[PDB]
Image (cartoon, rainbow, N blue to C red; front, top):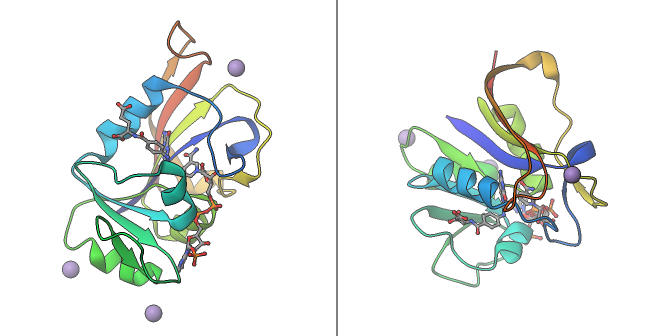
Length: 159
Ligand SMILES: NC(=O)c1ccc[n+]([C@@H]2O[C@H](COP(=O)([O-])OP(=O)(O)OC[C@H]3O[C@@H](n4cnc5c(N)ncnc54)[C@H](OP(=O)(O)O)[C@@H]3O)[C@@H](O)[C@H]2O)c1
Ligand SMILES: Nc1nc(=O)c2nc(CNc3ccc(C(=O)N[C@@H](CCC(=O)O)C(=O)O)cc3)cnc2[nH]1
Ligand SMILES: [Mn+2]
Ligand SMILES: [Mn+2]
Ligand SMILES: [Mn+2]
């Protein structure tokens, strides 16, 4: 099973200048809980944005060019990325925009955080047909001293 996980600001913005400009510790904690002990697939730009391997996860990087770091696994196609995960129950696709576009048609589950923040961005999450997806979990949180915007955690499953 393939799942996508992402945090979306207003208008589905997910990044600007190869960065995420907000800081929401509760959402990073959610990301870690839902990805720990699973393989994660990311594109090369997202790998450069994160800047280090994510511990406790098999890190698989998509790039057309040879890898430059043997602490992670480098693959050259979507099918190779999937195969490099082995026989696991759930593969997590962690972006960015181009990668989410390619894996969305193959995904059974979306873990989305909707952030109440207006962000100038240059990268968006793919337009997804709402009729295809059932909301199975949602949890709203007001802003607090640690998290400066309100946010909604949602899990959607393909109908
Ligand atoms: N808010 C969130 O949840 C979230 C999550 C992840 C990322 N982001 C943001 O998203 C942005 C990065 O997204 P992005 O769309 O620019 O880049 P991306 O999807 O991270 O990376 C694209 C790169 O991945 C490689 N790639 C993708 N598909 C491939 C394929 N089928 N075969 C081989 N290589 C493939 C290519 O690398 P080569 O050029 O080396 O071939 C391509 O240039 C940043 O702003 C980041 O902060 C946000
Ligand atoms: N919901 C969600 N939020 C994100 O921030 C996110 N980020 C990415 C890609 N970028 C990043 C950037 C940093 C870290 C990171 O530092 N993660 C630590 C945080 C642990 C914690 O704060 O408790 C990790 O071990 O996962 C992960 C992904 C992909 N999907 C996401 N999905
Ligand atoms: Mn092929
Ligand atoms: Mn197999
Ligand atoms: Mn806000």
